[PDB]
Image (cartoon, rainbow, N blue to C red):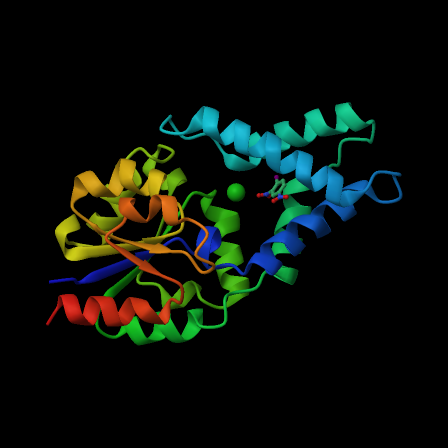
Length: 231
Ligand SMILES: O=[N+]([O-])c1ccc(I)c([N+](=O)[O-])c1
Ligand SMILES: [Cl-]
């Protein structure tokens, strides 16, 4: 049976408008009056961030805030603005202020929490991640919160999933994982026996649906999938 349901909250349950707005507001704060379009800075930042994380996939953990501060230092040198002090404080303030959940998230977590172990699996530094979950109001809706900082390795390394399952006290066969990127999922959770649910809200990832056991566009479909797996 399924006894645990795991999500990637800060990575996949934040609205698309909300995540972009947090990031844009960080760039605007960093730039101040400097004559660079913040949207252009954001685009360049995401490019360099994706590159930097790909270099760390599967590797031993290094604070993500340190990685992103390195990226911002390269951007400051590139465009000529002064490197912002306290970037991680700016970012946490903007996340707490403008972060936004998909509308069905609170309902879904509450509906599951009574009957399953509801867990979060996050590739974030634990302290800002947990503060962000607190600001969003869902921290205490989770039975467990597990991070790459706790596990010691970046995905697709399986240690983070091994730890999340240990916290729930079950083997992977008893657990579902809801994500939006199936490759860092498959490279880890598949070998542990977990059932994978891909969240594809706009149907934009059809070429990866074969890498997932179930595909949904609304998180309220998750309870129906698990309730039925449990007959
Ligand atoms: O998303 N961002 O734009 C962003 C940039 C830099 C940092 I150090 C963070 N942070 O604190 O995680 C976030
Ligand atoms: Cl982080």
